[PDB]
Every structure is written in C-alpha cells, then in structure tokens.
Length: 247
Length: 247
Image (cartoon, rainbow over all chains, first blue to last red; front, side, top):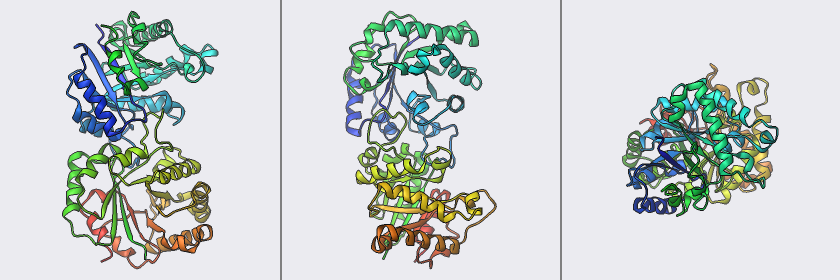
C-alpha cells in the first residue's frame, strides 16, 4: 500500500535552537513505524538538521534547488550539496515560488528531472488560485502544471505530489477533507491516463492545504489522500499528532 | 585609509570536503593584518564554514537573502539565519540574480535596507551589460542602480560596493585596471554628491570583474579600487595570492 507521508515545510522560519527542539522532539516521539516523515528547514540549517535526526522514519529535505548541480548561479541551492550534507528531498514548485518568484511550469519541470537524476526525491507542488478556481479551471491548471513535468519526467517513483489549494489562502475560504479527496482522486485519475494505473496507484498525493494537529484526523478515511505537506504546524509539537493522525 | 577588502563568491560550488580545504588553507596562510576577507559559500555550507574559520581577518557571508526576516517564503534565505550561524555579510544585487532571477533595482534596494537594519553587512553589486556598455550607458546604469538603493538606504557605513563589468563576461572583451579605476572613481564621486565626501571617502568599492592570483597585483596602485569580489579563484589556492596582492 501507499506509505503515509508527512512533509514539514518550515518555510522561512527557525533557528538552530528551535530546530534542535523540533528534531529532539521527533527523536523521542512515539510514531508509527510505517510512516515517512520529511522535515524541510531553510537551507542554512540542512546539515545541522541531518546531524540531529536519530529516527529512521525521519529524513531531511530542502525548500528549493536550481536546475544545475554547480556553476555561476550566485544565491541558489544545489541538489548535490543537499545530498552532500545528508538530505534526501527537495520541494519544487511550491506556490510561494510559482507566484512571488515567478517560477514557471517548465522551470519546475526542469528542476524535477534534474533532482531525480541526481538521486534526490522530489515533493512536487501544484495548485490553483481563487481566480482560477472561480473560473472553473481547477483541473485545467493542475493538468497543465503536471503536463509540463511529464514532458521531462517519465518515472515518478521518487516523487510525491502535493496539492495546494491556493484559493483558500487569505481568501476567507476553507477547503474540506471532501474537497481534498475529490481533487486528489481527479489528479490520480489524470496521472493514470498519462503513466498507467499501476504507477498512479503507487504515487503518494499529499494534501498541502492548511493541515494541523487538530484537523489531520479529519482526512484519515480519504482514500486518495496519502499524507500532507504541513505548513506552520510543522514547527510545533502538534506535528507529532499529524504523524499519528491515522493510528 | 580604506581597509583592503577581499570577498570570495563561491557561487554554486563546493562540498563539505572542498570548503574545509579552502578554510583550513586560509587558517594557516600568511595574510596581512590589515585586510578584511569575506568568504561567501552556498547557504547549505554557511554554518559549517563559520565553524571552521580560525583567522580573525576572515568572516563569512551569504550569497543572497530575502527582504523579510521570516514568513511564508518557501526556499528563501533570511538575514536572521545568517546572524544565527555566525555569518556577517550578504551579497545583494549580484548580476547573476539581477539577470537570471529578474531581481529588479527596488528588490535589491529593499533587501539592502532590511539587511542593514538587521545589523548584517552588505556587499552591494552593480554593473552594466555589453549592450549598455556599447550604448555608452555605463554611468546611467550604475547611477540608476545606486539611486534605487539610495531611496531606501541613507547610511553606507556597513556597505561595500562591488562593480561588475558584466560586459566582459563571455563577450570576448576584457576590462583593465585602468577601466576599473575610472569607473570606481566615477562611482565614488557620484555617491559623494548623495552621501557627502566623507562617507564616499570611507566606502570600499571592490572590483568585481575577473580577479585572480595572476592579475590581482595589476590593481595595486589604483587609488579607488579598494578590493575585489572574487569569483572562481576564491575556490583555489591562488585566493591567498589575491589577499596578499598589495604587500
């Protein structure tokens, strides 16, 4: 079956002291043996985070990387350097980068192929805005975003897809577990038409909307929801509750 | 007088092993007592670099940071993280980010004001392209870039300016020490009209064109060249020669 996957996107937050607390808590926490947890701290703390982890179920990932391993790209992160310090994943296509930093569909596709090629797992993010949602373009958007990646990537074995309901950010709107199940199902069905039912059935699709200790359990019976890409809750003790939400 | 300043921009290069070698060499190297050396490794190696440095003249800097200390900005570096791990500087406005990552004049200005406000030193980069050079817009460009920063920054005490002759990168053209002295003098005179002669006389203006162990010495008698923002050579043993180029 698809292994429950909980990613923790710290975003631009954390210090050596606060992250030490986050990791030590995970080191002593009682969590399922068959769960995959990936904490994603700022690049400045990747090495340190890896050094602190003493839990088999926990690995470390970066929040972004470039499409080349090295070169004259001042300010970027490299998947090879991420690997060098012991990290195992990289978040690509996060809505905050597609919007604020104008990373287009192909940029994300190019980064994904490169990361996978260097042996680094990818937490691929997709999602539509409120405007796109109201225009009834939800499927058109996620399909366009995925299609771009499919042009460069044929194997999603080392990939997990995170659906971000951008339309629910600061809009006074809220996505429900039913909303998640519906779109995850459509996404899985779409990817099956492009990669075949088998690959589609093995792909973890994570809910990337507001996920916390209080509401994680409300998604436990959604068949096509295989985990989460947690936001601010990943910096708190309740992150452990999310990991145990399907016990 | 102005203290000689040598920055080493590693760009997207390095491994824990290679950086250890670079830092250990600087630790045991014979360098001037009155020189400020700032090595700038990828964010992934900032903490490790600081931990290895044992030379008083050597400090560490990041290659880029956002204009906020924390928040929902997945993939960015924060000036507070720089301070947290003992780093002291941040490179802002490097040509590679202005071009490839579409960072405009105001974005750099905002980042600079924020970085300085947090007590982090800034290596402010400016420079014109081949087209701008050919159109004789060199001065118009550097002045435009600086003016944007001046709108937000009124004190350059904790700033060092790096002039990048982008027009000499992969174009078949080469800048000379005479070219550097001329533009540096013009930059200083311009800033003097805005910040006053005293502030301008204390400002370090670094040559950011191709600078290596072989040609560093050719800039020794140029009164307005106060140092370098070294590229590829900062990854090699000759970086030490650049640091000693004015003995």
